[PDB]
Length: 191
Image (cartoon, one colour):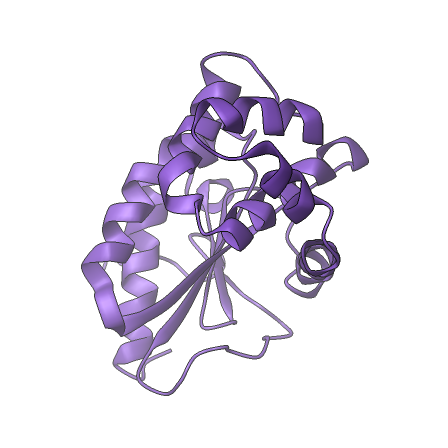
């Protein structure tokens, strides 16, 4: 408790909390991230394991972030993969293309060509990428960026009210520690 995360420092209490898209008994956890962000990439195995370990106790989602027009195709990519039901399978390879192969996947054609090597049909992918539904989700992700006042990635939000991430904690391990703390406090009705 002397070692407990410090409100204002290790996490931020949002002045305008947001609606929670989870039923009573589940804590909502949202990760704002960008495929091109080295910290988001390093954090993947850490957040994946933690999420799996919580199970039904939480409702977890990622929201992609496009800080510039050039990166909007990465938000389209995120939602197109989810639309095709292949996110779980191909996402590691996407991160790897960007961070290790130095392929930034900045256009729908570059994405289709790459995902084709991972077994995704090009025409199905492009039809998803260009779909009205994916367009809607991308415009929606941009509104969420504003609603949660997100200005760095990765940012973790708990129960629509508490934000943390390496910008607050310095370290990715610290981010995970703060997240775990916040969720338990929310469960205990202390936050």
